[PDB]
Length: 228
Length: 226
Image (cartoon, rainbow over the protein chains, first blue to last red):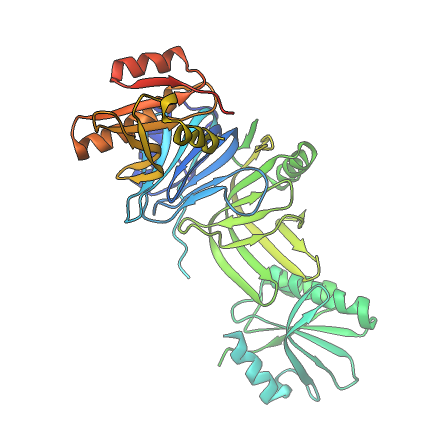
């Protein structure tokens, strides 16, 4: 048991074990199953047998996806209670009454995913650069912030001494390989637009060895700056 | 219908995505990752455990472990790409880029799922028009009637003033239909006493259905949708 537990086919014995396992440890259940769906809320509907993906989150979020759109086909908010008996039901009797049932026909697989909660400025660095472009370079003119480009968005964009377009990518932590690749994409996009004379300067307090490497390798520059 | 790799390398993921594109399956990745978005504005989410769903029509969804809505999503018709990150770009006239930079892929699942291809209201119409198809002196009163623990197709009152629950199915009535009706009947029995009848209205029913009905004190009535 690490972060993913799978049963490449479960029986009813298994599912109940796995749901409880998930409730116990606060994991996410994802079932792939041929099934049908029955809903009772404001009105009463069903969907016939078909292949669906069903996601049950620790806080009671319940989602039913079939294989086509962005939206789930049916869903239920945090705070809905989960129950099993050959069907998974999520009922919110939280003052409307609502019942969403997945009658499992054929459970292809169930996956428990013991996922950690996700716990939640560069605008101020930009302020510094506009205030005193000299932190970047002598005679650098910053022009745009969050500038839409053909293939992306550039933190600060300006023009240097020689009239070359200068792209700035601002990070506030150690700049990684990803940062450099991100900036590269912006530079290349603009190179396809204004010619070979576009500079990419990565502005951060420091950077990885890999970052420094790919920069040199790529003809791009670094500039040291602390979020004040 | 399900292919799993309980840990994939980059070699694997590319095989699996292509496998999925080829056969038109759904990819579901469980991964520690981070997310970078560029659309109207530019955002990121730090490292965390997320579920990523990639549908054959380009639907792209990123869920973390807490709300109903995905944390980031992309509509049908967005194009998918892999290089240590999965990207979905819609340059479909706004430009939008959603990137999952995979830190640690816990598992990837391909699910080769069939398209889903899509009345009892008319049966109800028949019943209100001529209650006699149910019974002599049956009065149908409500349609899609909200009840304490559910919704009743048709609800009425019989000759003797008993509450009558109708469950209408248009196909062979199964065990599930009977159980469904039972729930409604029981709910109402806890409300109005023991004198509530449950009549399953369908063109026919399983042996199991006929059984559980008899076993349960519930009735059947034969009726064909138009």
